[PDB]
Picture 1 (cartoon, chains in turn red, cyan):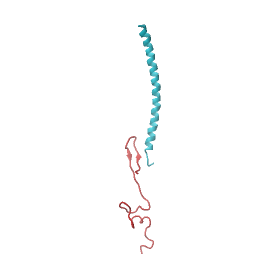
Picture 2 (cartoon, helix red, strand yellow):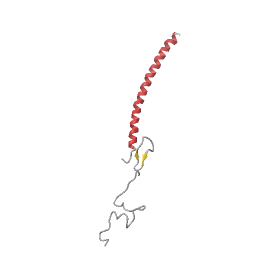
Picture 3 (cartoon, rainbow over the protein chains, first blue to last red):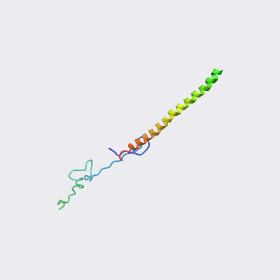
Picture 4 (tube, one colour):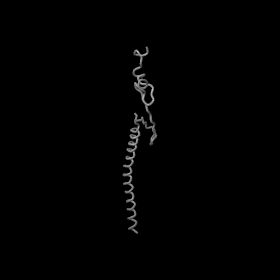
Length: 51
Length: 51
């Protein structure tokens, strides 16, 4: 579901743009990861969990 | 000869009324064009998805 912009007065004179981020915008491979890589932007350990 | 003379003048007037009719039709096609241009524009921007 790209961001097709119309840019020209003719066919296929267009630009495709994509965008993503949310709470789970930390490290990623295809998905973020489980215990890491999203909750490093949603949960962010230091509740007691560095001592 | 008279037959062809008078009928040839009247043939001129016939062609002239033909011109007139065609000018009317064509004017309708002018305003047709202007409208279709508007349409094309509305399609281009309407094809400017994303915004």
